[PDB]
Image (cartoon, rainbow over all chains, first blue to last red; front, top):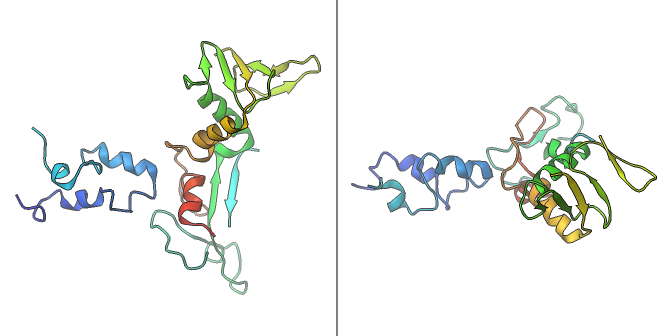
Length: 51
Length: 100
Length: 51
């Protein structure tokens, strides 16, 4: 259940508001959200699979 | 006419997705001439022909400027009228716009 | 659409040129060739590479 030991961590850290790698291209911001990894939602909610 | 270009401080931290164009490495200038790292960008959508077409397509599609046929254009002068198409416009001495 | 009517407003024309041509929210591909830098639109050029 640990955050660091989670398999989604390399993608979840790559997709966040803090991360400036996405900010270069506006099209890239929509690309990650469509693959269920939302940068708007916090890390605890982003990693968690709803229902 | 078709495309618009913007080509132009020192040792700035540039993103990985965008590359600084070096005229010496790209075989555009020799080694004897001083090094020139420039920001080279070209957009077809901003070129005279494409810009006029893309504007009318986006402006008239929006509900704000279109009201069941009439497309309000703020760029065009008061009283000026033309057919709703991206065709070439020629001004006739009659006081009307000839759209191809 | 059938008829285009001129309203004559520069400030409204500027905002439309900005939202459509200069700084579009959903811009065109703008590919990265041997001669091109890689920027998608004008707004991103002076934001990260101003001189």
